[PDB]
Amino acid sequence: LGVANILGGIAGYEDTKMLRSSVGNFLEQVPAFGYAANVGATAYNLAGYLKADTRVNERDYMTGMYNTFRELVPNDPITQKLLLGTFEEQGIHIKD
Amino acid sequence: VIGAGVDPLTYVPIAGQVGKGGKLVNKMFTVAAQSGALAGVSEMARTSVAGGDAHVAEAILGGALFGGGMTAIADGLGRALGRFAGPATRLEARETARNVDGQDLSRLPIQEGEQTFSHQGVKFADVPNEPGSVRLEDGSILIGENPLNPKTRQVFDEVIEPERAAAGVNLGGLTEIGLKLLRSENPEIRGVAADLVRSPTGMQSGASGKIGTTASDVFERLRAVDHRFYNDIDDAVTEALK
Amino acid sequence: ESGVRALGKNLLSYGRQGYDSIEKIINRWAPPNENDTKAYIDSVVAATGIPATQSLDLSNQDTLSALAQAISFHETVKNSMVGVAIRAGQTEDSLDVIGDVFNPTRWNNHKWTREELDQIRNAGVLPQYYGVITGGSPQNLTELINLALENQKLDQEKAKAGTGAQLAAGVIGAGVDPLTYVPIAGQVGKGGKLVNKMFTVAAQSGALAGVSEMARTSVAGGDAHVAEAILGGALFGGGMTAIADGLGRALGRFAGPATRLEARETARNVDGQDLSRLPIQEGEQTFSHQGVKFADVPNEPGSVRLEDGSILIGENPLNPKTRQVFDEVIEPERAAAGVNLGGLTEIGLKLLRSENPEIRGVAADLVRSPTGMQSGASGKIGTTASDVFERLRAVDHRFYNDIDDAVTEALKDPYFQTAFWRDSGAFRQDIYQRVSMAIEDGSGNLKAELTPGELKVYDLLKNQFDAKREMMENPAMFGRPDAQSIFPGSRFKGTYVPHVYSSQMKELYIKELGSPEALQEAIKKSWLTSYASRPEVKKRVDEALLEADPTLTPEGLAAAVDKYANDKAYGISHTEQFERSSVMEENINGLVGLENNSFLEARNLFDSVNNLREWDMDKIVPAYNRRVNGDIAIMAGTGKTTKEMKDLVETLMNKAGDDGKTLRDTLKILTGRARRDGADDAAFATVMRTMTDLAFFAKNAYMGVQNLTEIGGMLARGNVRAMLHGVPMFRDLAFRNKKVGASEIKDLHNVIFGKELDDSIRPSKQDVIDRLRSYSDLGRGAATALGTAKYYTGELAVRSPFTKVLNGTTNYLLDAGRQGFLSDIVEHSLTGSKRRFDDRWLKTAGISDEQWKGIKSLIRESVTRGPDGKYTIKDKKAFSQDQRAMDLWRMGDTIADETLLRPHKLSNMDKAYGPIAKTVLQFKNFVIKSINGRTMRTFYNATKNNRAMDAALSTVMSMGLAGMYYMAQAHIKAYAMQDGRDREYLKQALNPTMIGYAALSRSSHLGGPLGVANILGGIAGYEDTKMLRSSVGNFLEQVPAFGYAANVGATAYNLAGYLKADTRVNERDYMTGMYNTFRELVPNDPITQKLLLGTFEEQGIHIKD
Amino acid sequence: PAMFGRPDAQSIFPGSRFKGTYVPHVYSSQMKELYIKELGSPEALQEAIKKSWLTSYASRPE
């Protein structure tokens, strides 16, 4: 897919900051359904597009950052042990 | 690993404990009152985990093992000949402080009377005894190989790759273009300008623009939902190949 | 401020540089090598709450201003033992109780998702163990679940051992020790009862049928919960008796009711002798009030004896003597005549005795004459208005009794118990809004989101809302075949939910948009979009338009749609016909609104506008029901619309110019327009009058009712005894002998006027309250980052920790303080005084000059004060419909909150204090003493359950506050007696039992938001049916084949359930209504009683004598 | 496109009477070259496509 697609959703925060900067905002309440509850595969039909929340929260940061670094840092320790053993047996350049 | 613990070079893990749910807590950086004790162990017949909230805490567990091993290898070679120790300690201090809501012991604040710089609105100052690194405003240190290091981006864009300059990779968004467009005198252009873009003259004081959605609003809504869709299809497909 | 203002900036810079904890700041402030810095850290940790290592957040005022004051303080005969004793002590800073026990700065703010709630639900934890989970972080879910499961297992084993089963044998005689008994949680539904061995013969009660297997048992709703509520009451009574005996023996100087209660219950469970009766002998003196006889009791003044020897204490709300004394001497204005309802029977009897044929022609059809009993001359055609009215009114009250039990169980899902960032009063509005939105949806994705506890509410509401419309469309299903339909628009199908619009939201939107025309255009376009998108809306509008207009043009739709929608938009943006004030206005003087039914022109063809609606069903459903029932009855009985039955009255009165010789009253009572102020008194009077017949044809209900009411009275008495010895203002008002003079009447009448002023203006929605509380925060200080990111208008954590930890208790104090400050503002506005007003208030609240000038002008315009000392308001409906009322209310609330509730510790409070400020301060002091005790600390350490403490501590506020207003009203009334009669009046009015009665009858136990007038209002049918025949016997009818004992819930309320039901009274109605009325005061668990008992032990009560 | 707030917008979908699910069609070029080599002329490819289309009309009713 690519980093341009996985992590490309945070431009909205910058786009919304610069609008006002260059009786405050009359802040709006979320609908009765807090958007924390969304059954998967039913948040993307026609009804899910027209009545959603389009601001950035911490979940986007965490999910995008984890997806970008998936195959390099998995959630199992065997690969690290194999690499460590190989580098022990063959040796590395010590500089100096 | 640092202090008292396992021996990194002789430790073989067991397969199958992926979803049990664990975390890193080091006893050398906490007071026993802050982290009381352990709530026993799992029954090992009931546990389950979600997607990404409880997987970062195990990815970091793997990273700790790798760092400790590399430090041991380098120390052995160095002692043998006669001549990876900072980042490992900093990482373990950060994680232990994060899990139990305690002090962060891995910070170095900026004093007074010391030179500072800035690039793209972000300030920083150099760190002594470790060339290539940098300090942020609140005393967080990043090694020179991080993708978020301001000094390395500065040195690239200045001296190494001027053709691929920041101007060649800059996107400002619809905001600045709209602001420039709305400052016109030709009525024919303004007739469509008033409808294409959303002027910042609102904030409960907008003269006009009340009719409904313009192009900007629908564009932003759709572009905001699509990226979530992609982030979900990736995880849906990845699990199918097992 | 007016102080420090330097350490604040220093700490701002320090927090900007990135310093976390106390240790780092202090070590930089004073190097460790030069001077100690070991006892300089403890003195700061003890006086602030935050432990040394734990992280900080210097962007919160609660953590900033608190820390600044704890630093500046530290910068700046004697031979025998006295010299050493005084000269050796040193002063230290005061403690912070709230932070030490709860520690609320470590609580994280994370919104759990669906999967993370399904995991908890599938684990299998019971509702009383959610205390551990709340406030945690996402990485640590599984360990917390394991901890809860381990605690559950340990408690299960302890209960199997047979530890908390010694309460079944009773307290009096031989049994447990009341003051050192600790119950176990989780045995709610096992099923137990009280049987005392001292009042039975061993042959009558043989033995025990073993014990439960403890893995199978279950209980019903109300039939097997009374037997445990009474178990709790017994423990409370025994504890109070022990405390009083100890105090009395100590000094040198609650024993009847406890013994009587235990004797009654033991006699009830095993069908034996009742040893707690004292019959009336011969030669005694007897009285009567409202047809009920009684006689006095020796050695116990204030009590009374019924005909069969049952004794009731003086604070029971069924006591005839206290009602007699009230009605004759104390409150003659609220006389029994002012609270009497006779019903349709007497009015019909009077109406039928007429001579005018025109009136008789309609009288014969409106009412059912008693000349029947198989001898009725006429009236055989079918149902008249009376029959349909009685049937519908009989089924509605059962519906109300069921909706409460349905809703109450919904608020124990983990979704609501673990959210500490929202007020605890908006949960019901949340439930009603979500369900109502899900009903009107056609797709179905919204229905899939509701929790497993809301589907039953969904079913009930849907079924009834369909049944009512089905009845309104065909009113010939009752027996008259020439009746038309009254539903406006009946071609298509759907579910109708009433529409009621707000006014404050309209004013706030008009202020921002600048004109009503902007609102009209917004409404119009938000309507047109639905026509554009959905197909079914297109079909409905097109069909209606084409049948409305004979001309057909393919071009004409683009004009017809708009010229239809414009009128409907103008109907809301430029008038006030559909607002809540006019539709639901309290009282009318005559028939003024019967021309048009405002509930039914809110219907539209279309499908944001939902921002101007109201979602409070507990007040909206009954009024709709009353109006609709009246219309249906009139139409199905007579064959004429309500407008015709209205204008007939004036048509008749046009010929009544001559002085020749009740139709209006009959129509008024049928429609549902009679005054209904103080219906709770009538509700209790009905039971008081018909108790004997219940005692005749049923037995268990009799004793159950008696025991419930006695427990309530005992609780009220104990509370007033404690409050006398606690709070000084209570003592000052309760111990007078003569008329007060000169000054104090002005304060006593400001106390009265504050409540009315607050009640007439308070908003009726939640979003308005949120916005009004949000403006004042932005009036002092915020940033751009606060506007973006999370923040959100949902605000409870931004407040002090006092609101977080104990939320239910805080609302009473806040609502007292607001009323306190409003009257001071008004008085300064009128008289120009300066003894109370302060000019820092404008800057603290956030009021500029223009708002203050407007407020002052309005108050000077609309209110007058008299030389007597009484405030009067000229206009009431127009006064509460201006923009300035919201400004006034916001100012009062902000000032009260900031000045009284924010600053913790008694050393942080800084011109003068009024009559209500002292009361609030003393109540807060009582609470602070209560929390610091050993009992609450041990309970919290054992189980991390903070929900019980708030529930236990709300009742004392709820009762004391009502007592204060009763006393103030008595004093202000006794001022006008010119002669020496005031001494006798005050002797009669200020007895402690009288205070206890007035405190229990008043207050907010009721039945909750619904009310006693609704929960217990269904027993009027028995009285209505007795009087008909009294003023070949009845040919008694058999029940249908289905005995009505079998009715599957939510299917007894559809159309079929209304037309073929049984409409007579049985014991189940008595038991269910009585249990519902006394729910929160006497729960079916014993922990709350133990907490109250421990507190009253530690603090002590007034022993009288 | 009138779901968003402007009531004088038409439709842009070409062909909207019936119902179905649309999945985008993108054709390759190397396979076209290989088949042209095997068959010898573009006309052979045209006839093959035409007949493979007509068979579905022959069989299915919808």
Image (tube, rainbow, N blue to C red):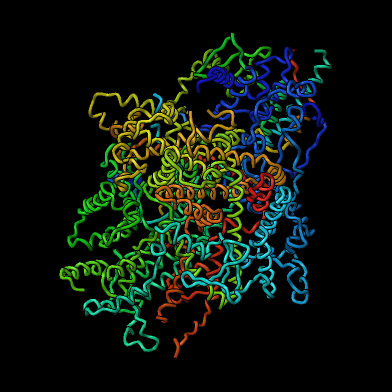
Q: Within the image, what quadrant is residue C112 found in?
A: top right
For residue C818, side relative to residue B146 (left or right): left
Residue at image point 37% right, 85% down:
C372
For residue C825, side relative to residue C563 (left or right): right
Residue at image point 52% right, 13% down:
B158
Can you say whether C75 is above or below A77 in the image? above
Can you say whether C489 is above or below C1099 in the image? below
Farthest residue, direction right = B80
Q: Nearer the viewer, residue C64 or B175?
A: C64
Q: Position of residue C2 (x, y in %)?
A: 50, 21
Q: Position of residue C850 (x, y in %)?
A: 32, 29
Q: Position of residue A11 (x, y in %)?
A: 47, 31
Q: Nearer the viewer, residue D24 or C291?
A: C291
Residue at image point 65% right, 33% down:
A72
For residue C605, side relative to residue C12 (left or right): left
Q: Position of residue C579 (x, y in %)?
A: 32, 51
Examine the rendering and report whether any part of residue C573 can be seen. yes
